[PDB]
Length: 51
Length: 51
Image (cartoon, rainbow over all chains, first blue to last red; front, side, top):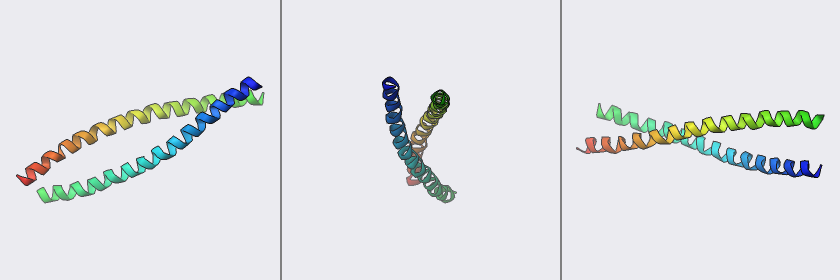
């Protein structure tokens, strides 16, 4: 039970690290998706301008 | 027996996160690579425009 609790404690520690890292990775993925759509909305009025 | 059942579902979850992570890391590499070339080709459209 002590062996198991020690491995369970490691799984828990890792599951927090994955859960905090993914919530910040996702937030930069939604910021990056917005800066791509924005830089696209910019660039198409430079394609319209070059035309 | 309940722990054994749980230890199977943790393995399924571990694998689902490991696969999701690998693929997402591939997509992130493919994404950073095209934002370098798209920006290099835009630092040339700025020179054709200013020309």
